[PDB]
Amino acid sequence: GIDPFTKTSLYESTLKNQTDLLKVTQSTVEDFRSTNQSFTRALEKDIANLPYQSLITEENIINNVGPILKYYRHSINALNVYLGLNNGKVLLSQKSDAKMPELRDDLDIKTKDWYQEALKTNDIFVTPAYLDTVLKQYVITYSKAIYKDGKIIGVLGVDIPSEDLQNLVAKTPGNTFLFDQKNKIFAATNKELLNPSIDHSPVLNAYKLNGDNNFFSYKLNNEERLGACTKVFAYTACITESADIINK
Ligand SMILES: [Cl-]
């Protein structure tokens, strides 16, 4: 309407609404990451709790670590779960025909960020989404250097399809969406937003001007829209709507 009291009431209401919904999308991304981190941490602990004898020959790694990788992979429906060693080999449990985990020598692991970055932090390392060479799907990898008595055993990796996060975000309420660390569109409730030719600059420009969680106005085709974005790890989560709620 027109009376400023009424317009202010509508603006304050929709701000709260849209903020709530943005937070649900933020929570979705957070919970996905923390579930995968907890899992990875539990797997690290089970591997490190084996005696050294079970860890210090490749055959013993196959027979003693392999089943653990397999059970864990199944438990969460991961794509791959694996352990990379300093000799460049990887003990790999992959989705497939029920064949046991095997040692693979062709994964060029000392060139891979999941391997090299795990050795530079004491935390879990989380990759951007990338194309997994084993099963040829886009994954987010959680990796962790495993130590026993201070001694490196190898680098654990857990590959989760990136589509799993995309699908979780898409199911959320609200016209919410998520950009990756390069500010490309990554997930959206409205699948049309994923058209790579769409211009997101008005929303990204408005976020740059306003900051995390700060509700803003912008224009599309000379009509007014409202929205907000916030950082969530290296992602940017946004929500937008028509301003007709406050103007009409
Ligand atoms: Cl994540």
Image: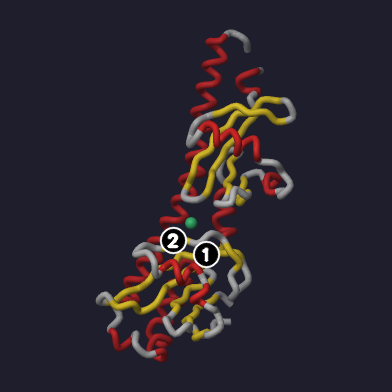
Respond yes or no on whether mark 1 lies under 8 Å from ligand 1: yes
Quarter of the picture holding the C terminus? top right
Residue at disc 2, secondary structure = helix
Q: Is residue 170 above or below residue 13?
A: below
Respond yes or no on whether mark 2 lies under 8 Å from ligand 1: yes
Q: Considering only order in the chain, which callout, 2 or 1, is on the residue closer to the N terminus?
A: 2
Q: Amino acid at mark 1?
A: Ile
Residue placed at 63% from the left, 71% from the top? 136
Tell me if 197 is positioned left or right of 104 in this view.
right
Residue bearing mark 2: 36
Residue placed at 31% from the left, 74% from the top? 147
- Percent coordinates x, y for residue 25 in the rendering: 51, 44
Disc 1: CA contacts within 10 A as few (<14), some (14-19) or many (>=20): many
Q: Amino acid at mark 2?
A: Asn
- Percent coordinates x, y for residue 5 in the rendering: 53, 10
Residue placed at 52% from the left, 74% from the top? 111
Residue bearing mark 1: 160
Viewer-proximal residue among 233 and 170: 233
Viewer-proximal residue among 130 and 136: 130
